Image (cartoon, rainbow over all chains, first blue to last red; front, top):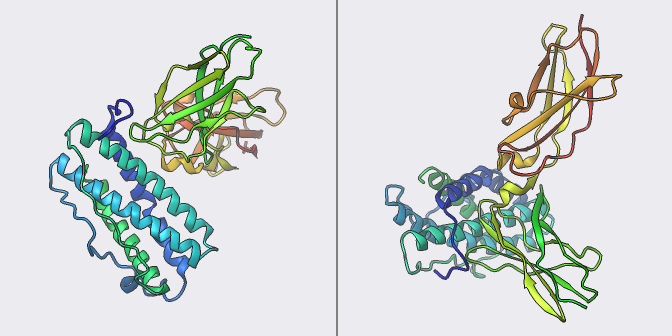
Length: 169
Length: 201
């Protein structure tokens, strides 16, 4: 909760705009990703790119504002880190998917901004003290294929969860 | 020689697609070697300082990419052997400082079976997915020295087409259009490529 100057007074409206932004380009990010992987992903989306809530952080759209922002926070962090690994690998495995790399970063940038804003309402309105950590375990735990799949499943989960988040605030 | 004056008139612009750029008025010549530094920071993160080049001493294009909907505080620091001063700070959401790309693919059609009617269609710049658009639609006869404009209020929200009417029959017309954030906070885009069309009689 360290601040460098006064947080903005239209935070909730801004994160709403940020969630919409995410939600409105997630489908394109997903599509870009599998299309860039090639066979056998485009044809087997259901079993290679489904939305698996593995260790993925929870979200109770029915919670209080404070509780949702705290869950949203852990989610963004999780996505944010999952996104770094995905891009790290994708720049190696598919060095040619220029468009893909680009949209990955663009989404990573939007996500950081969301963290800032969420952290700001959480500190300014709820004096939370701080929020608890939860990262995505990228690791070398997987031959090229498991990376591609884990990646594709994350984005699959991302596309689904984001929509749920986008209209719960 | 003299110490640096407080820089002023700091203003930033974000051309669609590009990184932010701020400019400012340096002040009275110091006669000394004076360095300018553009500082910027979210409320939770200090960004990389931007040091103005000699070529362009009173302007800086940051190195981080533009993130909308997150207020960013910005200011300029001036310094030389005699003093180190900073400008007043400004704090804004980059969304209100955008200069979209011009709408493109403007084209004319007579899809009305009537004379005094022409319909324009175009493709909006990508920033449409972030901001609601406003437009200025200009038209004139093929052979006319100045442009005429359609009332601003009639083209005040995003759209990809407009049908111009009350035009003179059997006349050729030229068109151009530009856009910017719907609330007027930002910068007008450059004009689109012109498009022509004639009417029935």
